[PDB]
Length: 37
Image 1 (cartoon, rainbow, N blue to C red):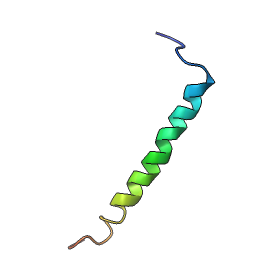
Image 2 (cartoon, rainbow, N blue to C red; image 1 turned 30 degrees about the vertical axis):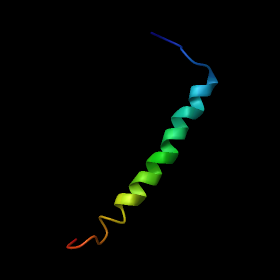
Image 3 (cartoon, one colour; image 1 turned 60 degrees about the vertical axis):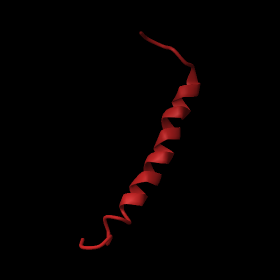
């Protein structure tokens, strides 16, 4: 399996990153003083 989608997916890969950075922020605030850090 090689070459399935055009340049479209190129941005999709970036689409997920946006969510990823959003995720780390969540933990970075629950791992920064949740109770007994």
